[PDB]
Length: 124
Ligand SMILES: [Cu+]
Image (cartoon, rainbow, N blue to C red; front, side):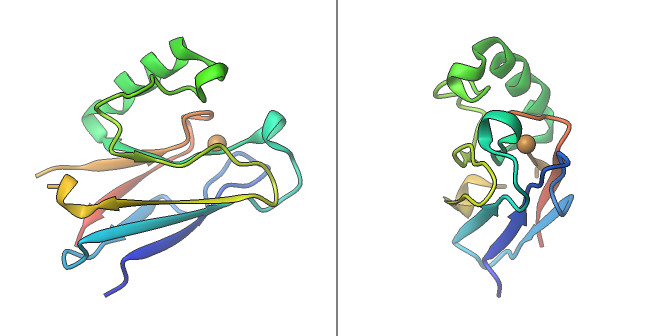
């Protein structure tokens, strides 16, 4: 089984996939985010955030209110299962999480800085 995924966020405010599959056998899962292109993080920075689909809008609302100073996430938001740092072009970050925190239950990933950038994460 594959228990990681490589995802890209580019200068055109897009991830290169809208769906991630987590094998049901994985006990941990790693997301390796990178940023092809050339725009720095103060122009077009990206992160990767995981929550349930049901919680996404709530996380984004409270993130927006928290602002740039907090990378557009409410600090310690219990709805956020995992997240990366904000990265600019040429930079990378990885986050690993325990699959036991996933159930049910439909999950989504998104960029907190640019919440139009989204996709689904599913156990398979
Ligand atoms: Cu982004």
